[PDB]
Image (cartoon, coloured by chain):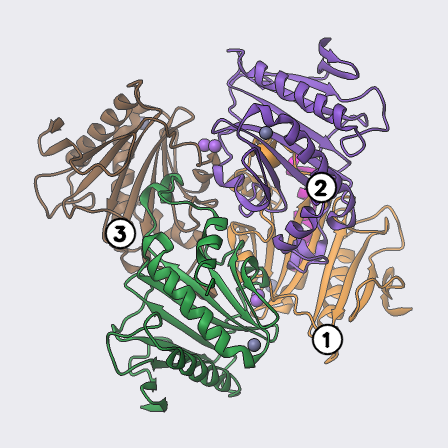
Chain colours: A orange, B purple, C green, D brown
Amino acid sequence: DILATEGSIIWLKNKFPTLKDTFQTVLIETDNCEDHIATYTEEHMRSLIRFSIKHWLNLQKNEEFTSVILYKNHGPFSGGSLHHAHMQIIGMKYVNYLDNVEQDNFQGVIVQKNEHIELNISDRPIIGFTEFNIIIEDIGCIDELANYIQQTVRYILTDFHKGCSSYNLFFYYLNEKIICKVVPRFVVSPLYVGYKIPQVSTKIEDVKIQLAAYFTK
Amino acid sequence: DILATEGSIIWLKNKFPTLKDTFQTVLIETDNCEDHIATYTEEHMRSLIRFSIKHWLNLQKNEEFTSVILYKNHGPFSGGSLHHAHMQIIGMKYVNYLDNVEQDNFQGVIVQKNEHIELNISDRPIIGFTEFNIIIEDIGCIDELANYIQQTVRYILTDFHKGCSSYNLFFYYLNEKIICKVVPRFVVSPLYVGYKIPQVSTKIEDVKIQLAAYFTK
Amino acid sequence: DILATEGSIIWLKNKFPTLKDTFQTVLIETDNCEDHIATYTEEHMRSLIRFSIKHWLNLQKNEEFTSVILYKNHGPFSGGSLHHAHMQIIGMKYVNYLDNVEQDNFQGVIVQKNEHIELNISDRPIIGFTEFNIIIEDIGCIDELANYIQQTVRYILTDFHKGCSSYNLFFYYLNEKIICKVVPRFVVSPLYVGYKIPQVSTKIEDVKIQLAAYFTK
Amino acid sequence: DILATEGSIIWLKNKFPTLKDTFQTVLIETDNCEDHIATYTEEHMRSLIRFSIKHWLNLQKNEEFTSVILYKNHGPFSGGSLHHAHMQIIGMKYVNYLDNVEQDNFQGVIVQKNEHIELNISDRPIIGFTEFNIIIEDIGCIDELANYIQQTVRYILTDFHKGCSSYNLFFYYLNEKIICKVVPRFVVSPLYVGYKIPQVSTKIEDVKIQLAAYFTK
Ligand code: NA
Ligand code: NA
Ligand code: NA
Ligand code: NA
Ligand SMILES: [Zn+2]
Ligand SMILES: [Zn+2]
Ligand SMILES: [Zn+2]
Ligand SMILES: [Zn+2]
């Protein structure tokens, strides 16, 4: 059942609901099974983030929900399902998604920052690994957000851990700001899990330097 | 190249070394590709842990190594490689595996405890999720350790998260004690990663109760 | 300026406000400078918690506040000011005190539990040390809460670290439950701060056993 | 009982031992009760750190100790005792002070860095608050370490939290490096302890900027 569409962007009511007291929906990003965020043109990436944010924020205005979640799963280690490039909008009747997240989960080491947008790496992440926070203070900076998401995603798929293949996008409307948390997803090394013996560098300053090389142009 | 064998238990020098200044070895647990820890007889489970611990502790006595690691990977989310049931012994020339682990990573909520052995759940885990610590104070309690590993593994594969399919074993020789940390491995739910919205119960007391039901006999 | 009184219990508008966009108040617990929670009779402890909770919850109903905080400071390491036995009620126009606290900060190792009340020790504390959570699901169990606070306070001042002298009380209205978090306050040992070398036992199970000895009667 | 002296620098065997299987000593920094690290001349600060490090590292060479700790307590919230400006050297027969500290407790956000020395703020602190790590890779850079300690201390006593009055110094000999962890000590705000409502900025990037202003000359 079609909720809204814009070209190849399609917003569907999820046919397989698994969460009680929730309105589950799926957002198809393209009519092609090859393309994703790293491949999309600047216009398609701009239109996709504008469509997603608009329908997320307008559904929250519906008094039948306490809060509405907007998020993405990509790769076999994100927790997704469909092979097609898609996002999800879940309206929740009794759950407030901000409840168990704090302000300091979105603060950190600045990679890029100006009056319009801020890109940082969490020094107090939600789960304890790498989390990239992209914050805008005005809705008019949505095209800047879309560009920062695309570059951070491109970095995760290409240079972070010499290619990571899986990630998540999480959106938040907190303190009148729109935040996108970009989270790489990977099977952690057994030597790190049991003995905190890293293979690569665990330095947040090294991630900062190599991610900053994606905003040099 | 064969290092030691005992029936179907085979200790091999790893033919694909990927870590410099380390002696990598593989320990094949059975001559069958169907059996694993949850399936093995009490005798085979006893013989496998006795063989593994003996060769781990004797290799550390070799002055060419600072420390020697004994660990296992099981399932597609552990970080392993071979489909066959195997463990690994890695001799490290300049690394001490205890360096970045602390005493409190092995303390916790007691599930089972007596003069010979202790089974607990980490209240200060190494990575931040569920970690089962099995501690013995004397080498003579090795058959008790083997039984506790098998039951904890059986619980992880059967009831924890209604079946977990993947886990890790990590062995430590700390404060003159032999510790086995049993760690379930699973792709964390996206709603938990980004919003700490759990699907199941996150209560350590609930895990304690349902794991204790495996030691009722 | 008197807001409400009940015998020696006096609710005053704080004459020294230091927080902008907040209504600061002070709650004097007794007309004596010798008595405190550990000394008070069962009736005075019951009347003090009933008065405090009632005025805290009724002030939150005032549309001029986003949230209202109810808390106590005791001893020279709590962050208090007056030597007299007092509590504080702070009405906040734009701050929601639940924002940066999560559900798991109130879960833990059960010390005492029944259908009416639950006493636990945080396995995921807010700050990282010992935190005692006393939870009631119905307002009618307020006299049970008052008794559990008094015993937990008595334990902190007497046996925890062989006498702790300082603590905090924090009240929360979360998921239709009334929670009191009892937090001991002490200058942490320098050997622990810099090297995690403890003087006493850091085991949550040992605190559980010795606190349970205060509910044996 | 005098162990070593250099002008007003006096190394004494602690007359009040309270730790069994340890050799406790006290290091008096000056013959005056007014002076401390922030006041000392560049020469006295250089001579004090050279004397302290030399006697710390030489005592560890004594086979009667597993490890030797070098640390300082300053102010009423550090955990010290004497009002006089002093440090402590504790030889421990069976304890290795590195056991429960990891490599990542000394990594972080770089404030100052060159080939000789590195000053950072912990992104993974030992206790969870602000920790300043000063690392040198060669013993010849000891006068640079002494200057960085003095400036970081001066900042803590003057601008951090508009004056902090208390701090700790912790020294470590790890991975053939000499590390000094400078830790401010203060009574945490009750609104932060119970509700993570900060009074000041909790941003590591703000501390980085204002501490960097002490190395502008
Ligand atoms: Na909350
Ligand atoms: Na260590
Ligand atoms: Na929140
Ligand atoms: Na260790
Ligand atoms: Zn803009
Ligand atoms: Zn035994
Ligand atoms: Zn009741
Ligand atoms: Zn130098």
Give the residue number, with chain letter if any, for mark 3.
D166
Distance (Cα) linking label 1 and label 2 = 35 Å
Is C3 in front, or is C217? Answer: C217
Residue assigned mark 2: A157
A207 or A64, which lies in front? Answer: A64
Q: Residue furthest right?
A: A1
Q: Which mark is residue A65?
A: 1
Task: Tell me residue D179's x, y (percent).
Answer: 36, 33
Instruction: Please determine if labels 1 and 2 lie on a single subunit.
Output: yes
Residue D116 in sight from this viewpoint: yes
**Prevailing secondary structure class for the magenta stretch in the rendered image:** helix
Tell me where the magenta segment starts and ends, as one range.
A144-162
How busy is the neighbourhood of tag 2: few (under 14 within 10 Å), some, or many (20 plus)? some
Residue A151 placement (x, y as % from top left): 67, 48
**Dot 1 amino acid type:** Phe
Instruction: Give the secondary structure at mark 2.
Output: helix
Is residue B18 visible to the viewer in this orientation of the structure?
A: no
- Nearer to us of marks 1 and 2 is 1
Please state the chain letter of the residue tagged with numbered disc 1 in the rendered image.
A
Task: Look at 50% across and 33% down and name the residue there.
Answer: B100
Q: Is D32 a magenta residue? A: no
